[PDB]
Image (cartoon, rainbow over all chains, first blue to last red; front, side, top):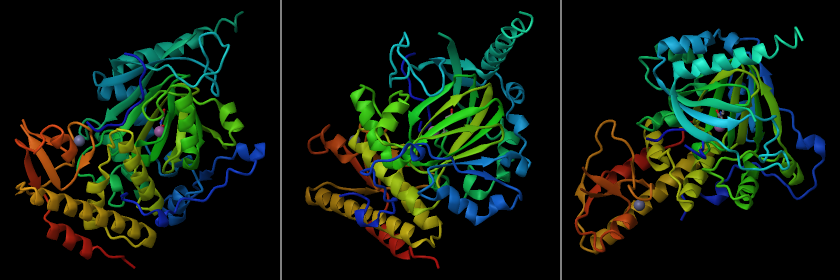
Length: 11
Length: 455
Ligand SMILES: O=C(O)CNC(=O)C(=O)O
Ligand code: NI
Ligand SMILES: [Zn+2]
């Protein structure tokens, strides 16, 4: 879904 | 073959060739106070926030100047509004503000570790509160005698039922700051882009970090600090974005989708002015179009944010540049710029001549591209069905490359949509590919000619 989010690195 | 005409750039002209002294390498952040409530509704305010020269702006104590009921966004108000609502979590390492280090503090590094996980709001509220009480204890001793943190990020207050009073409150804002507004490009998308044209909530603890970025498609951002702690902001003017991206390349981190915390000395070393400022409870941050920024919580606090699309030439030009650049980089543009431009021309009167010429150019190119695509499909014996747009039909995207697909849709089967390349390359002659047309040449042509400059 177009959605705004934070970059990620693990998980 | 761009949707942009280089001659029409309204981008401010900035010379980095000349050496720059340090005082200008630390520009003052435009802070604005609102004695009257109608000041907030003044056009000069909007002119100010959207001025290209003004990368970022703080509106001081606006949440009292209009009597916004922030208290509602208090963690307590939230937990009981719905605690078993859910939340993305970042696990991070707590550090001083202007710094990010390897495991030992030998070196400053660009890569910012930010691992991901999930909880509920009620659960993160526990954590946020426990965390605060703990820091309290370690101070109620001294009196009488690596930190791992979790950041609650991009929490979606989209459900206008559940979050009714919270959302209703933000109606009290000047139109250009609102979630939904006739003058908001993002209100003309025809569907929901979570976090852009809906509200996101941030639950932070001290050290809680949002790493370097520009907004999706270079859209303005509006952030309010709920309290009770502060936030520290860093920001650079769009002009310098490629220089920052270059750093990301050298340090092996993707600029657009990677996690990175800039090395301030690098930026000073590169002659790049950095805005540094503190955002206090009830302070609103306005991030102008294309501004590189990154953010640290210094206390315990929640923020609220969403993206706005004011109808200015600057905002528009930058939305398009990022739209094209995204596809050069194989990165999904979540604001379907071409579908938006047509929606805007068809629903909104435009008085600003520079913005008008930009939308007009884009529509033209959209028509030529639709025209070219039609001939060669005809020319090669391909039949094209006519499909209507229905009411509240969304924009489409290539199931494969994520590019926006406009007007002409390639489809397979439980049905999938593709751009032409992805359809061919998956069938040489487009066999088993239905092709749909949503706007006949004449629908677009008439819409185009109907589109004129308002005085
Ligand atoms: O509030 C934060 O932690 C980060 N927010 C933003 O970068 C924004 O609203 O544009
Ligand atoms: Ni941001
Ligand atoms: Zn494709």
